[PDB]
Amino acid sequence: GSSGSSGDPSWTAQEEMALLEAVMDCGFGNWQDVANQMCTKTKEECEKHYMKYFSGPSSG
């Protein structure tokens, strides 16, 4: 029950949405394909970050 209200001094609002879209457009594990719209960062960061907030206990 959350849209995605949480900024970051590193990532941006666009990156967040882009991360999901790619994750749903391509699929999980395809850090490579996802890097397409996430190019803004390293496929490695797109993963850790994802599991950070999305796959996290509390907003963060």
Image: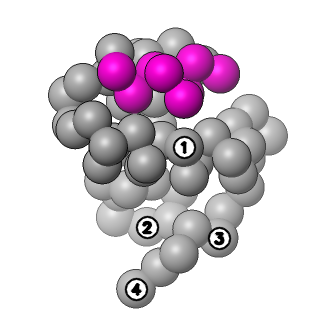
Residue 7 located left or right of residue 57: right
Q: How is the image coloured?
A: one colour
Q: Does 1 lie within the magenta span?
A: no
Q: Which mark is residue 5?
A: 3
The Cα atoms of the two marked residues, 3 and 4, are separated by 11 Å
Q: Is residue 2 above or below residue 55?
A: below
> What residue is shown at x 20% (from left), y 28% (from top)?
29
> What residue is shown at x 54% (from left), y 29% (from top)?
37
Q: Is residue 44 above or below residue 29?
A: above
Point out the tag, 1 or 3, that comes first from the N-terminus. 3
Point out the tag, 1 or 4, that comes first from the N-terminus. 4
Q: Amino acid at mark 1?
A: Ala
Point out the tag, 1 or 2, that comes first from the N-terminus. 1
Determine if residue 52 is in view. no
Q: Which residues are magenta?
A: 33-40
Q: Is residue 53 above or below residue 5?
A: above
Q: Position of residue 2 (x, y in %)?
A: 47, 79
Q: Answer yes or no: do the residues labelled 1 and 3 have beta carbons within 8 Å?
A: no
Q: Nearer the viewer, mark 1 or mark 3?
A: 1
Mark 4: give few (<14), some (14-19) or many (20+) Cα within 10 Å.
few
Residue 21 located left or right of residue 26: right
Q: Amino acid at mark 2?
A: Ser
Dominant secondary structure of the residues highlighted in magenta in the image: helix
Q: Answer yes or no: do the residues labelled 1 and 2 have beta carbons within 8 Å?
A: no
Instruction: Kindly state the secondary structure of the residue where label 3 is placed.
Output: loop
